[PDB]
Amino acid sequence: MENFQKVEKIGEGTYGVVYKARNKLTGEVVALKKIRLDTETEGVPSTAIREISLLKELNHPNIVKLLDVIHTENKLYLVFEFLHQDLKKFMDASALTGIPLPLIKSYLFQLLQGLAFCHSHRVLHRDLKPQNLLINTEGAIKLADFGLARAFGVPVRTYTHEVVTLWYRAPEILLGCKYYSTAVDIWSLGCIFAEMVTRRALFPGDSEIDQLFRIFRTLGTPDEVVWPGVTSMPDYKPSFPKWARQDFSKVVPPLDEDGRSLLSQMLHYDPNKRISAKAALAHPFFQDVTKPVPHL
Amino acid sequence: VPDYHEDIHTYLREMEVKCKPKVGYMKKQPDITNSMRAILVDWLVEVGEEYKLQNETLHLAVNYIDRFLSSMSVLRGKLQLVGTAAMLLASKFEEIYPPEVAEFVYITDDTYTKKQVLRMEHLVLKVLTFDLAAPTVNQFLTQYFLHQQPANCKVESLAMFLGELSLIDADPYLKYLPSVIAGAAFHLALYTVTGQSWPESLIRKTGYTLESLKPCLMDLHQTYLKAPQHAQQSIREKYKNSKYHGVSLLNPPETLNL
Ligand SMILES: O=[N+]([O-])c1cccc(/N=C2/N=CCC(c3cccc(Cn4cncn4)c3)=N2)c1
């Protein structure tokens, strides 16, 4: 750590504060994650044990690069490449006008290629959300924060006590299968796209159940036609109120036909039909993607 | 969503080569021996049984242990410590949340202090340079299992069992890639339950002809034949339970048709 000059704090996440900091020898700017290393209670946290081993294999433009781990006795330091903002912030700083169409279809494109890489390396992110997407002033945008990611060499069993987030969480989990799939990453991305479109969280629930119900209010409540399985999912109830699927162009006015087609496949109820990252990248909506920079 | 299976499968394969241990290494440990290692593993199986850990967590831990052994000399005195550390990491990586260190410490009959177990996890990490995401036979079986017609869970159990079995003996099994043993296992298990065989699917997926499998088959069948005399037993007792259809009870079959 000799050669870092801490420059200012720029966030926490999860067992650690993030600094902006600069390497006094190369001049490179970086983002340091400092970990609480209690060498008497818990040892290395399980997040940091994921984030690192995972990221250390994923090397790629829309995954945040992990430069180096300084492993002292009492301190663990993760050196990341450095990105100036997060999409959450951007969108906040930018609602009122909204993020430019073009910028949006760029972002989504890139997130798809990031994720698309993640899955094809047997690696699940689970925690998609604008706070965990970092952008830079060249109009890049990079999956980040892998403390929740799991390898799925074997299927990944659900937390009953999901410490996971609302807001962006597949209905299949909310009805409590005992596994995650690729699909959940997509579902989140889905919603982020929406939000980016419409400058408000597509599904802002206040509880596991409000959240189901907000989705149902938008997608309309699902049946067995639409989602073979549902009626027999642990959290499923014939209690549920029937809502009626809504015209998307109601939800995402600004979106053109191509966009909406993409969205509505993204948000498919059936994990088994919901489009993959690979496949989305091939969607028509991407046709005239470019690379605008943010107004940062 | 068979959109990834292939990519993945292939990645496993490429990985599984990098993250492999040194065949000839028990031989350079001046103070430990294969036997001792068998001790340690059976022991983990058990510990895994007690904290209801998944099987993968186990696979991982051994992996760790081997690699770690694979560049560190360690006295009979240290090794179980090494185990624990691996067991702890592995859970950490693998499980939804692990046991707390303290438990880990306690399951060794307070023989190492919680501090040393800490000072160890960190040493392991340091030696495997956080390369924790290792491919396991389990990982392999699981993909493998996708290609059963139909599925049939005796087989599945049987295979895992086989699987675990080989965890135990560096002996022969270090000589063999996780994906092979996998194969061996699946097909041993297949044969055994159904008298059917290693599906062309899988030969096509894996490029493993049944022939190629044959040397690792021989070993494994023997292991299975003797399983019940083995010096270590934790694994059997484990696949005795209904959750596995006592698969392990049920009889090896005496010849392989080879
Ligand atoms: O909210 N941030 O973490 C944040 C805000 C603004 C700029 C930031 N810059 C970087 N640069 C490099 C890495 C990096 C980062 C890497 C991993 C984890 C985190 C922390 N975190 C990000 N989302 C939730 N927690 C940040 N942030 C980060």
Image: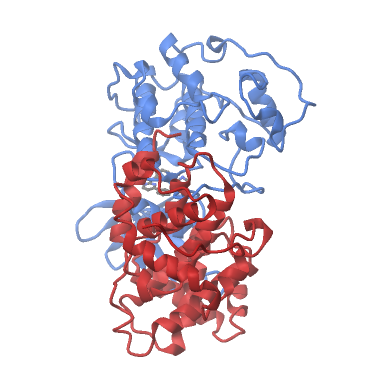
Chain colours: A blue, B red
Q: Nearer the viewer, residue A251 or A242?
A: A242
Q: How many marks?
A: 0
Task: Please name the residue shown 37% across and 35% down the image.
Answer: A116
Q: Is residue A72 visible?
A: no
* Residue A25 image point, x, y percent: 20, 61
* Residue B84 image point, x, y percent: 51, 75
* Residue B200 image point, x, y percent: 36, 42
Note whether B3 is above or below B213 in the view shown: above
Q: Is residue B159 visible?
A: yes
Q: Nearer the viewer, residue B6 or B171?
A: B171
Furthest-left residue in view? A26
Furthest-right residue in view? A239
Q: Nearer the viewer, residue B116 or B159?
A: B159
Task: Please name the residue shown 38% across and 40% down the image.
Answer: B201
Note whether B167 is above or below A123 in the view shown: below
Q: Nearer the viewer, residue B258 or A195?
A: B258
Which of the 4 quarters of the picture holds residue A26?
bottom left
Q: A283 left or right of A190?
A: left
* Residue B184 image point, x, y percent: 40, 58
Task: Please name the residue shown 29% across and 84% down the image.
Answer: B28
Question: Where does the C terminus of chain B fall, quadrant-wise?
Answer: bottom left
Q: A60 left or right of A36?
A: left
